[PDB]
Amino acid sequence: MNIFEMLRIDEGLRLKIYKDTEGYYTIGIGHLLTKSPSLNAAKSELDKAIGRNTNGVITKDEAEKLFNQDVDAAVRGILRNAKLKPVYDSLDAVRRAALINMVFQMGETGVAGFTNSLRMLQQKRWDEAAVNLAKSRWYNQTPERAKRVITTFRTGTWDAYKNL
Image (cartoon, rainbow, N blue to C red; front, side):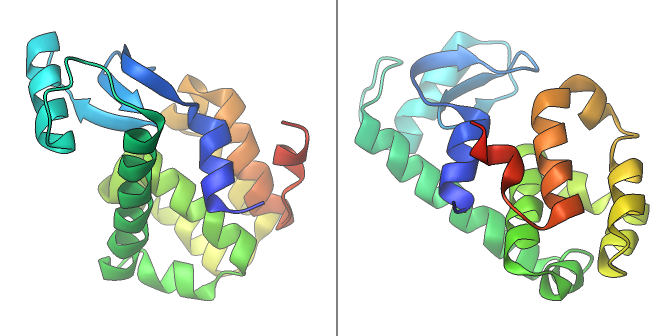
């Protein structure tokens, strides 16, 4: 398993504009288009994103190309972030995938806010950190996905995804 397969499981793949769990306009593999309520604002961001008149529908290839960029941007974001970088550097390869997953979902800013959890991860207190991460809107809102990510941090294995 790898970050790509992992995220592909957590986000799914949709070739037509859809609303995400928060009610926002999304397409492909969890690619947020706009927080705006206008389907029209969404289609416009979409076309700009793809470079063609999509009319709200994209191909598998287009979806994947957006996905590749988003993963790259997630990694680079962590590497540039002063709160995130040190945690990332401290982690083994599987857990690193878990931090990338959070960042792809909630943005750099969002994850950087999990101050206490970040400190625990850095200190390698797995169980403690898993408990702290669960005390969040994040866990409350998307508990199935949050549980898979948390288990990944707790065990350092891909068990939670081997199921799926």
